[PDB]
Image: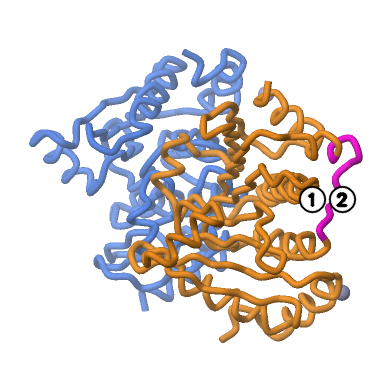
Chain colours: A orange, B blue
Amino acid sequence: MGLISDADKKVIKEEFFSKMVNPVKLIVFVRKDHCQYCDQLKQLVQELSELTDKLSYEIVDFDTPEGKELAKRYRIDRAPATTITQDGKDFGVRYFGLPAGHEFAAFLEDIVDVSREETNLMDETKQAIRNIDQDVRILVFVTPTCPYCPLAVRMAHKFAIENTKAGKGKILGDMVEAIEYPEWADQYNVMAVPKIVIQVNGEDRVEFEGAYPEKMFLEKLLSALS
Amino acid sequence: MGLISDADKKVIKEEFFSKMVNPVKLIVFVRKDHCQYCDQLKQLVQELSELTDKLSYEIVDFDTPEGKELAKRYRIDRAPATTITQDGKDFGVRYFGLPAGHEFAAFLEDIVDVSREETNLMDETKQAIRNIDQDVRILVFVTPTCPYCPLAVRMAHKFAIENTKAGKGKILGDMVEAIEYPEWADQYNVMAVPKIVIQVNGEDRVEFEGAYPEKMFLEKLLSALS
Ligand SMILES: [Zn+2]
Ligand SMILES: [Zn+2]
């Protein structure tokens, strides 16, 4: 039932989904082993798609040969994962795990921006991001209780949307819910969050902790591109 | 080196350790397998004991038959764990994992209260806590980035100190650093923190999320004692 209260539904419809333009499809990858919150993720996306005719979803079994083929196409290497697409078009906007806590609002805002295919990034930032031609993966490790984590996840996602808009689609912005991916978090000594890891061509280049303002965050990414 | 800066040392000495009365001994349990931050914990306690002659420590290897005997005596069932004692006397004040983030200040405050063998708990709360005669274990799951988590950990620890003072010593207040104990956190569906689990006689009785004020927190514990 109410993973989303009826009062919440009204707010979501009025303050978020009323701003949608193009149809968005939530492609969710799940599996049978080690998916503690997979059912919650499943029901969340289903309840959200009932609030508007511009939102749809597709549940994919990562364990199947079919799911593996789809994942590869969407550059997904783990499950649970959700990529927010514009009618199936990959925008590099992904969430690994459950978007709980204030990550929920970031999830909704991401849906709107992919739908609008634009962001509120500063002009200078947009110019730089749209010029990036290298494969970049931005991992943003977060925990459910983290006031500033959403800012970092949204920044990574705005970068991905703009690069996709430019026709490159080379930036992957990945929110990673640490509680659900302990081995991955441990790999990067994640304690304080948000912890950001920028990889270029599959190799680590820059790692830092904290939600940095737009200008400083951009600077970090550009420096990793050296 | 500086897990603790020299400026930090001055603050610690002046605002915390200057208030100590009786000697405190930090008994730390470590192991070889799955102790990612064991070395950091080790160096932290060693650096802290250098700031005052009223603080000492003892590193115990949980893997050894000797360490297992000591752990049993200190009611420790996992490693890494640190119990804050008054010259070796068990006060039910434990930390499972690294006291990073603002848990560091809570760690220092706990050292002072065990040293003083008293707390700032309200009179009514003290009266009720000192009367508890049942075995109670309060688990407080936290993450490094969690503004209100320290409040809950300190409340659990103040309860343990008072019950020990009363001559009962039946309350165990356990801070559990979720990142380091994922299996344990998963067992209790820990997402939002702090998540509190109150067990009486080894069995779960009450589970809730959030730092509740003193009165409400006490109410929760008493209700589990029914
Ligand atoms: Zn409104
Ligand atoms: Zn001062």
Q: Is residue B181 magenta?
A: no
Q: Which residues are magenta?
A: A117-126
Counting residues from the start of the chain, the first of labels 2 and 1 encountered is 2
Depth check, front residue: A17 or B225: A17
Label 2 sits on residue: A120
Depth check, front residue: A103 or A114: A114
Q: Taken as a whole, is the magenta stretch helix, strand or loop?
A: loop
Left or right of B78, for residue A23: right
Q: Residue at x 43, y 69 (%)?
A: A61
Q: Residue at x 54, y 67 (%)?
A: A28
* Secondary element type, mark 2: loop
The percent coordinates of residue B87 (x first, y second) are: 29, 30
Q: Residue furthest left?
A: B65
* Secondary element type, mark 1: helix
Quadrant containing the N terminus of chain A is bottom right
Crowding at label 1, few (<14), some or many (≥20) Cα neighbours within 10 Å?
some
The percent coordinates of residue B132 (x first, y second) are: 34, 64
Q: Residue at x 51, y 16 (%)?
A: B2
Q: Chain of mark 2?
A: A
Label 1 sits on residue: A165
Q: Residue at x 22, y 43 (%)?
A: B74
- Type of the residue with mark 2: Asn
Distance between mark 2 and mark 1 Cα atoms: 13 Å
The percent coordinates of residue B96 (x first, y second) are: 36, 44
